[PDB]
Length: 414
Ligand SMILES: Cc1cc2nc3c(=O)[nH]c(=O)nc-3n(C[C@H](O)[C@H](O)[C@H](O)COP(=O)(O)OP(=O)(O)OC[C@H]3O[C@@H](n4cnc5c(N)ncnc54)[C@H](O)[C@@H]3O)c2cc1C
Ligand SMILES: O=C(O)c1cc(Oc2ccc(C(F)(F)F)cc2Cl)ccc1[N+](=O)[O-]
Image 1 (cartoon, protein in one colour):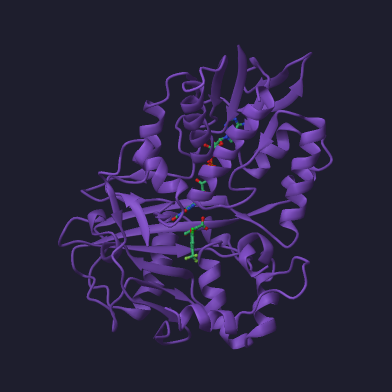
Image 2: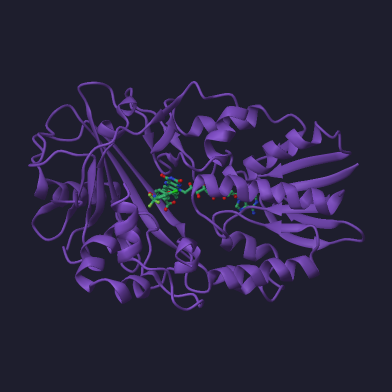
């Protein structure tokens, strides 16, 4: 009876754990699997807290619906009876002192192919280099750059074209809170020995088995290992492997998320839409601001207005250290500059993410390939995936974990 240990209890490890069991009980494989999680809870980046009839997503808000792996899991986990799409609306981009809106199918699918031709060279390059090469700087700075930074929390002059938009070579959630998706999995796991509050500190080789040194001192044995912990932790369990250097040299920008609850002192700004992002040249502290209510009404109790502001950006990310006070102050200080805030926030929830935004820079795919290959020839049966490899989005993480299950089995049986 072969053993497989999954390291990391976020969505990737959980996804791997869930589809691993589904496989062990459909081919009746002599496999016994266990999952180790460092923190006392499972779900990692996915955290949903409730306060005063509110539902605030400290981190992962929702997920792209077109990515099957995500809603698909929801079904298998039996939870479609909670899926709620986002309530569309207009968005804006605060340039200097003005809320401009985005511009006004077939004409769009074609305007893009004209504006953004496919890549000439086959060498990786930065998103900034790619755009700046075919559109004016002003455009990149005031429109493209603000958006991209908003969904990668990175520096576009560093981010890889190949790893973020390989194609150059509408959202769902759970009315109960994304965190339920995580809890639902933990409960439906039967053959998996889920150990929390324990961290793997070293990956090694015994005789015919792999040896996993734990926090406490216990040592587990395994024939196959799926590592889903973030680049820093992972690179630590295999510091000797030369290619692991790619993993430990990665960067994860720090960012802050601030939820705000208002009875009505909100008094809409000039315009009225889902939210907006701030352009580089704008000397603002906040990065973006979304009206949670408008998009996800089920978040805030009727009569209440729930806002969400993001802070911290690649480069100047020191704002994440200041106290809730300093943050919640800086947010309103800036927030008030484009809307009237009569009164004070009834509810306030700050939440920091120190190095939680994995950054894929130019050459990311090549380096990841080398690592996979190095691991294939020196550590057969060991696999590393997750937001640090190919895709930070929840859907992407789910299959990365699915692919891991696939590989591990092939190696073990097939
Ligand atoms: C603030 C924030 C907002 C986000 N918003 C969105 C969004 O709106 N939409 C979207 O699609 N994505 C969003 N994301 C991204 C998404 O949450 C991640 O891509 C995804 O959760 C990564 O999952 P993972 O399982 O690979 O890793 P993680 O969730 O990081 O989990 C890895 C696990 O490894 C454990 N671990 C680490 N070291 C050890 C050790 N030594 N031993 C045992 N366990 C260990 C950790 O405790 C952790 O639970 C957001 C992320 C953040 C931080
Ligand atoms: O950086 C992320 O982890 C993160 C990814 C998202 O996933 C997408 C964002 C934008 C798009 C786009 F641009 F194609 F619409 C697709 C996806 Cl899957 C959304 C939001 C965030 N975020 O940090 O706020």
